[PDB]
Amino acid sequence: AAFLIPLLVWITTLPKIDRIEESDQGPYAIILAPTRELAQQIEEETIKFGKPLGIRTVAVIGGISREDQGFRLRMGEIVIATPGRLIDVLENRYLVLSRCTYVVLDEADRMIDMGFEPDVQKILEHMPVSNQKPDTDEAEDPEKMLANFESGKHKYRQTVMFTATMPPAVERLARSYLRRPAVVYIG
Image (cartoon, rainbow, N blue to C red; front, side, top):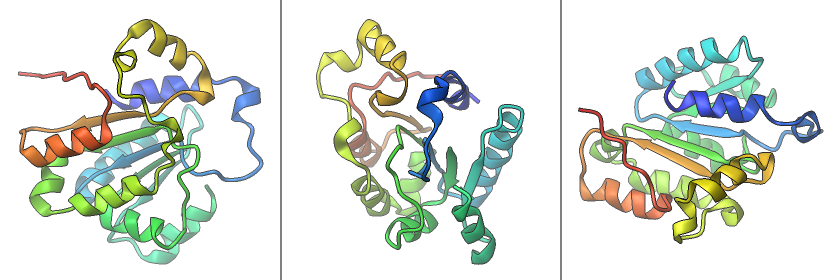
């Protein structure tokens, strides 16, 4: 919920003229999890937040037969995925990443310890780089970034990475994905 709530505020506080799109231009949000169990937990919690708000959530995971997930891909805001199944989607064109402005990597150290790093880098390679933050101090200024969050649809992307340890590979993923991040430590 600590990453879902600002996403829900951003989605439910758009104007009605900015939410209308005649085609399916992909998700507003990609939430990638290394394991099927954590993906289903974030799935169930995202559903129980999103059903009173009318926000659809699509699970791109393993263990479920391909007909059900494929039929859910034809319906078209939030997609929670596993990396191998998501890269099998992105390399075969079942879902696009056009209007994606929100990337969350939960347990990236578990992604490194299992070895999904070039796969998630190739998932980055499908992202349009037109909404990437500049590598200046203006990515951490609350006035300009607050007014950019108030701009609605045409803001830059935001990436939230939750981890437990610090290996250098998570540091390389941070230097590849993030633009001056804020490190919130609990404990």
